[PDB]
Amino acid sequence: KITTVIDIGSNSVRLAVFKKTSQFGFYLLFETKSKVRISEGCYAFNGILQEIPMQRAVKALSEFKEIALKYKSKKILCVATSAVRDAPNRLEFVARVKKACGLQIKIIDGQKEALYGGIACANLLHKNSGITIDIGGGSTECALIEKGKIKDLISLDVGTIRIKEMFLDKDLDVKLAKAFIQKEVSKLPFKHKNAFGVGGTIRALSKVLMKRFDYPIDSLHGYEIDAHKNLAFIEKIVMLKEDQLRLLGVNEERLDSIRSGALILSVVLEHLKTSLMITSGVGVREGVFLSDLLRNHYHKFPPNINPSLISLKDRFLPHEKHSQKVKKECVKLFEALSPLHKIDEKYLFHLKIAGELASMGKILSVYLAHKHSAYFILNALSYGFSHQDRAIICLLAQFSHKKIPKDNAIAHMSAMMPSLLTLQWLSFILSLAENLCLTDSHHLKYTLEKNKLVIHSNDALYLAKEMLPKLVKPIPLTIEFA
Amino acid sequence: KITTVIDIGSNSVRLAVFKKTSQFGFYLLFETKSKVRISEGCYAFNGILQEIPMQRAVKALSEFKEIALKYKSKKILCVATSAVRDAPNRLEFVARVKKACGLQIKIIDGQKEALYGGIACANLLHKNSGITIDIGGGSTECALIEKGKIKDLISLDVGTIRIKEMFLDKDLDVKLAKAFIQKEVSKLPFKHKNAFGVGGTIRALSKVLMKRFDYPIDSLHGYEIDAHKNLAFIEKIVMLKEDQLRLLGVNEERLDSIRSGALILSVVLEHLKTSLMITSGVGVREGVFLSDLLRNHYHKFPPNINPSLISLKDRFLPHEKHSQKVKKECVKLFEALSPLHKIDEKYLFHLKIAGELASMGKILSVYLAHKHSAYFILNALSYGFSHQDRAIICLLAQFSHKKIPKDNAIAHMSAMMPSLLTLQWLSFILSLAENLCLTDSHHLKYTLEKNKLVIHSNDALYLAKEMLPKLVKPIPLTIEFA
Ligand SMILES: Nc1nc2c(ncn2[C@@H]2O[C@H](COP(=O)(O)OP(=O)(O)NP(=O)(O)O)[C@@H](O)[C@H]2O)c(=O)[nH]1
Ligand SMILES: Nc1nc2c(ncn2[C@@H]2O[C@H](COP(=O)(O)OP(=O)(O)NP(=O)(O)O)[C@@H](O)[C@H]2O)c(=O)[nH]1
Ligand SMILES: [Mg+2]
Ligand SMILES: [Mg+2]
Ligand SMILES: [Mg+2]
Ligand SMILES: [Mg+2]
C-alpha cells in the first residue's frame, strides 16, 4: 500500500513515500532531501569515505527511518550509488547504518542504476523515444528508450561533485576539465534527437530557463527545452561566479555543483546531437517503485493506462459512473459537428480526458467546481502529459459554460497551441455534453444540418433545455430537441 | 451516508445532495436549480396553480429524482413552501407528482419553514446572534437566534413574485407597494443588530455589492454587509430598469424578481434597525439536513465542533496523527514567544486551525503543497468561518517558510486584518512547528531569552537543524538547540 524509497546519492540523499491507490494508480505522498554529500574529499583518497560526511549520512538515514515509519509504510527499499559502490569502505558503511537505525542498504551498480532512470522515463513522460541523462554527484547514467523499451545502458564515471573536487577547485582551464569529460562521453554508442534530463543538477538548470523565459506553468516535470537554441547559454554557466548565479535563481545548496554539472550537460547534448531535451521530475526513486509495481507487466503500463490520470480519479472520484458517460457523449458530439469546426482528430485525447475530470473539483466545493477542476489538472496531471496537454485540458474545464479571453496566459504559452476558436469548440462540446449527462439520461443520438443541431432522445431533458441559454457558442448555430 | 433534499420553491425549485463523512462531518456533494416558477399567475386567482407552471414542476421533479438516484442516495426528503401550502389545489399537486416520478412531497407551514432557516444559520455562520431573513418568491421567513438557540419565528405572507404580480406589473407607485410591505413587516416583535440574509434574492443582491466594492474573496457565504452604509443603495435598485441591472451583474433569470425583492429587504432592515447583515449560502435545504443529523443533539453542534473543518479533514486526511501534533506545538511555541510579539490571544484560533490543515495540500501534490492547502482553505473552509478567518488561515499556510509581500490583496481585504508583522509571526511559528514535527519527535519544551529561543528535547533533530536557514524570521532572533 505505502512504499518508501531512499536514494543515498553522492550529493543528495533523497526520500520518497509512494502510495498505491489501484492496480496501476500511485501518487507521491511525501518527498524530502538532504545535502549530506557523503563524497566530500573522497575522490582524492581513491574513494575513501571520510568520517565527517559518513556520520551525517547516519543521522539523515536514521531520521529518514522515522519518516517512513511515521507514514505507516510497509516496505522500505534503500539503494546506494556511485559514491558508495566505488568505495573501499563500502561494506563498512552498510554495516554501521544497521548499527544505528537498522536499514539494509542495497548497493546498485552503474548499469543497474541507469536501468531505473529509464524505467521512470519510459512510463512517466509524454515521449517514449529518447536518451535519459542522470547527471548526479559522482556518475552520469544514460539509457536509450525506444517506444517504451530500453535498449542499451551505460554508466559514465563522471559527476558534478567528482569533476568539481579535482578540476574546478584548482581553477584549471575550463577546457582542461572538458577533456576528462570527453574521455568518457565519447563512448556513448547511441544517438537520438530527444533527451530526458534527470537529476537535481539538470532540474536546477531547467528552473533557470523557465525563469528568464517567463514560463507561465510552474511545473518542471515535462518542460521541453530546445537543445540547439539553449546550448549556447548552458556552456556560459560555467563562466559565471556565485553572485551571477544567484540572480539567475540558483538555490544556495546548488551553487558549488551547478557550474560543474552545467559543463557535463553541454558535452552530452552536442555528442548526442539532441534537438529537444525534456526535464524529468522522476528519477531513481520512481524507477525503484515502478519496477515493483510493474514486475508482472514487463516494466511498462498497458495501453491507454496513465498512472497520473488513474491515481487522480481514485483520490477524488472513486465513483466515475457519472463522469464516464460525460466523456462518451463528447466523442459522438465531436464527429457530429466536424463540418462546422473541422478540428484535427488528435484533440479527442484532450477532450476525452477533460470530460472525465471536468467535474472532479466538486470534491472541494460545488461552487466554482470547474475552477477547482482546472486547478487540480494544472497541478497534478503530471505523469505522461506534456505542459501543452495539461494547458489544453485545464482551459477546457476552467472555461466551461463561459468564453475564453483573448489574452489568456495559459492559452498563449506556446506557438503550437490550438486557436481560441478551436478551444471554444472543445469547451462548447464539453459544456453541451455536461448538460445532456446531468440527469440519468440514456442512449442519445445527435445529427447536424447547416446550423441546426438536433438531439434525438426518448428522455424529457427538461433541465437540459432550461440552462441552454446559459451556453457560450463558438459560431452562430441552433440547438433543437426533437 | 448520502441524503437528498428537494426544495420546491415558489420561484426556484432547488436540489441538494449531501454526503455524511463523519458523526458531524458533511459536505455539499451536488446542487442545482430550476426556474419553474410554479406560482405564475396564481396570486390573482386566490392561489390557484395554473397548468403551465405545474407541468414544468412535474418534469423538473421527475429529473431531480434521477439525479438523486444517480448519486446512490438512500434518503430523499421533499418539502414545499408558500406557493404550495396556500394553494386550493395543494392536494392535487402532491398526488400527480407521485403519478409521474413517485415523490412524496411534505408540505411545510410558515412557522416550520422559518425553523429550518434558523437551524442552518445557527450552525453554519460565524455569528450565532441574529435574525434570519429568507426573502423567497411567496413568503418571507424570519427567526431570532440567540447564542445558537432559536427563540421566536414569524412567516410574513410577502415575497418577490407575490409583490411583483400584483403591484409592480401594474406600474403602481413604489410607495404604494411599500405600504403592503409595511402591513406585514410591522408585526416583527424582535429587534437585533445582526441579520442573516437567506434566499436567492438576497444572495443576488450580495453579488452586486461584492462586484462594485471589488471584493477579492469570491465566496458569498459569510459576506458581511454594512446595513447603514448600503441601505441607501438597496432602495435604489427598485428604480433601475432591466439594462441598468445588467451592468450591476444581475443574472438574467433574476431580473423580474430582483427589484421587487430589493424593496422587501430595505423595509425589514430599517424595521429591525440592523447594523450588519451577513449573507448566507445555506437555507431551507441545509436546515432539513441538519435537523436529521442533529436530531440527538438538540439541533446544535457540540462545542468546538465545526462541520466544515471536520468534513474537510475526513476527505483529504483521515489520518491526522501527523497534523494533530503540528497544532499542539504551535500553542506552546506561541506563549513561549509572547514577550517578543505581544499578539492578542484570540489569534490562536486561526493559528491552531492552520497547523491542522497546513499540510492538507499534499493530497494533491507534494510540490507546492502549502500553496495547495491555501487554495483548499480559501475555497472550502466555509461553514462557521468569516471571510476574515479564512483569509488569515489561508495566508498562514500559503506563505509558510516564506515572507509575505506588502501588497497582498487578501491581506488588505479588510481594515480589521492583523498587521503583516503579526502575520509573519504566526506564519513563523507554524513554519518552526512544522520543522519540529517533521520527524516522529516527542515531548519537546521551549524557552525564550531576550532574542535566544532554545529548544529542549531528547531528540537529535538533525533534519530540523539543516533546514533552519531556510526560515523567514519576523524579527532578528536566535534559534538554538540545547
Ligand atoms: N523530483 C522532483 N523534484 C521536484 C519537482 N518539482 C520541484 N522539485 C524540487 O522539489 C524541491 C521542493 O519543492 P517543494 O516540494 O515545492 O518544497 P516543499 O519544501 O516541499 N514546500 P511545500 O510543503 O509547500 O510543498 C525543490 O528543491 C525543487 O527542485 C518534480 O516534479 N520532481
Ligand atoms: N446556496 C448557495 N448558492 C450559492 C453559493 N455561492 C454561489 N451560489 C449560487 O450557486 C449558483 C451556481 O454557482 P456555480 O455553483 O458556481 O454554478 P455551477 O453551474 O454549479 N458551475 P460549476 O460546476 O463550475 O461549479 C449561482 O447561481 C450562485 O448564485 C452558496 O455559498 N450557497
Ligand atoms: Mg542518482
Ligand atoms: Mg456547482
Ligand atoms: Mg424558501
Ligand atoms: Mg513538498
Image (tube, coloured by chain):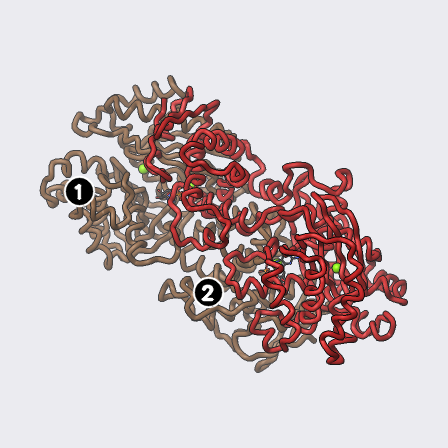
Chain colours: A red, B brown
Q: Is residue A31 above or below residue B185?
A: below
Give the labeled residue for mark 2. Answer: B346
Quadrant in which ligand 1 is drawn: bottom right
Badge 1 marks a residue whose secondary structure is helix
Residue type at mark 2? Answer: Lys
Q: Is residue A342 visible?
A: yes
Q: Is residue A85 above or below residue B258?
A: below
**Which quarter of the rendering shows the C terminus of chain B?**
bottom right
Tell me what residue is drawn at x 82 percent, y 57 percent: A110
Q: CA distance from mark 2 to mark 1?
A: 42 Å
Camera-side residue: B211 or A123?
A123
Question: Where does the image place residue B95, in percent across and percent down from the top left?
Answer: 34, 19
* Residue B477 as seen in the image, left or right of residue A44: left
Tell me what residue is drawn at x 18 percent, y 37 percent: B164
Tell me what residue is drawn at x 72 percent, y 41 percent: A300
Camera-side residue: B341 or A231?
A231
Q: Is residue A143 above or below residue A84?
A: above
Looking at this view, name the residue that lies furthest to the top. Answer: B99
Question: Where does the image place residue B319, in percent across and percent down from the top left?
Answer: 63, 49
Q: Chain of mark 1?
A: B
The quarter holding residue A16 reads bottom right
Give the labeled residue for mark 1. Answer: B181
Question: Where does the image place residue A425, in percent across and percent down from the top left?
Answer: 42, 39
* Residue B169 marker: none
Residue type at mark 1? Answer: Ile
Are tags 2 and 1 found on a single chain? yes
The quarter holding residue B355 reads bottom right
The local crowd at label 1, few if under 14, some if 14 to 19, many if 20 or more residues have their Cα within 10 Å, is many
Q: Is residue A191 above or below residue A471?
A: below
* Residue A299 as seen in the image, left or right of residue A86: left
